[PDB]
Length: 249
Length: 247
Ligand SMILES: Cc1ccc(-c2cnc(-c3ccccc3C(=O)Nc3c(C)n(C)n(-c4ccccc4)c3=O)o2)cc1
Ligand SMILES: N[C@H](CCC(=O)O)C(=O)O
Ligand SMILES: N[C@H](CCC(=O)O)C(=O)O
Image 1: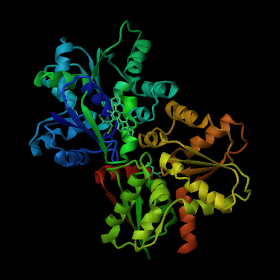
Image 2 (image 1 turned 45 degrees about the vertical axis):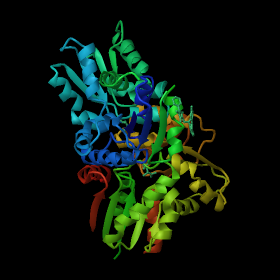
Image 3 (image 1 turned 90 degrees about the vertical axis):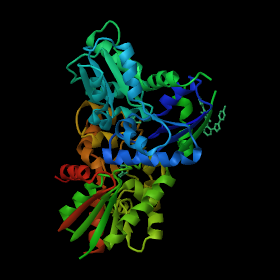
Image 4 (image 1 turned 135 degrees about the vertical axis):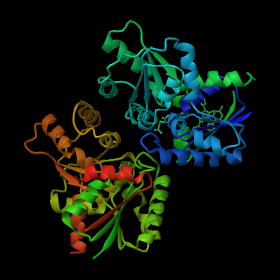
């Protein structure tokens, strides 16, 4: 069972981490479009075309399944890629909606979606959630989290000031926070720390992680069976691969 | 008079275009921002060099007489390769700033601080050019996060101040001259001035070198209105930015 994983860059390693721990696949071809990252600050037309070009990369690798680890590509390009692909394509949004259906029974629970500008602007999460009957959805583009995390700024004053900048205007205290971006799991503890410490909460809000959600879904569709992993990039492949160890820690 | 091209990785090049429009230098300007692939400064030399070659292909049907590479990163990494494969003159934004420093900084021991993207700083393009002119006291600092902050319009407040503190606190030298070696940095030039002035009891701010004003000065010494906007990403998104950056 040979599969491909597509991301705009290194963020997809957060999904790869979950896929490796699932012992579901024999071979994984990871491709990050690191020459053109980020996607989330760009426009739907551009991102759709990026997604179609990603299918071109995987043709010669004869994969049986393509995972779109990128939340931005999942939000803007997945439907377009599915129309032009003969093989199945799974993105990271729809499996997250199923995880919310299992873990969040109160349809009035305040849910906060965090993502790139493009992910939030698409309303992909809001639309899917509303389709399942959720009525209390807020969304917030937290663009600068992405470059901060890529510089390894995972704690301290800069992160906290950035976190305050985005979260201060919040009118509803969330019970659920969707980490609708590959990078955000790396600051999950800091995000929950912010809400406990600024809203005097007993426990933290519940965080939904895209990689864990897609694993749950994939396991419902594939038998249980350390896979072989290849790394490829449109920028320097060593600059990409050498960061894997730090993301898969 | 000359029809010219201006190339940048995205919208930052509007800081250079603004200077060009103020000076009323050229009759016709074709601006191209590679907004589908920005930023360049966080990527590797091989990638950036190829981006620079591809920009030349864009301008071929426009019959330009001069190409200004407004991007400091492309100037630092791709200019030589671009000039090799192009029939038309190409001017980047690094060498005109060296000329500006030579005119404005007569003390070869004056502490000069170069700010730029990761790729611009790693290239040592500025340090090498300054050393060849006899400057003896050069420091450099990549300030990568200034780029996304400025593109989000974070031009004041606690987040910008904390980011400046993050990059500048480890500095060992107090600069007399600061090179704004990135298209985006003129938009926080007053804040950078204010950082050093406050944190260091300076009577006057360090001299800031603006790439756009330096290249205007240079072009006036060599070549003693219509603008069109093109983009690899959505062109209306780039135009919306043009209105804000060029105001
Ligand atoms: C068991 C094994 C087998 C082959 C190699 C190998 C081959 N060429 C590299 C290489 C070259 C340059 C820069 C970085 C690396 C690197 O190390 N690449 C990683 C891989 C391939 N894998 C699978 N992982 C990983 C996965 C999960 C958790 C932690 C690490 C890597 O980090 O390494 C490493 C180990
Ligand atoms: N991979 C993107 C984050 C980085 C980018 O903007 O490309 C996402 O999951 O939204
Ligand atoms: N235009 C780039 C900044 C943005 C980027 O990294 O592409 C520069 O002047 O260095």
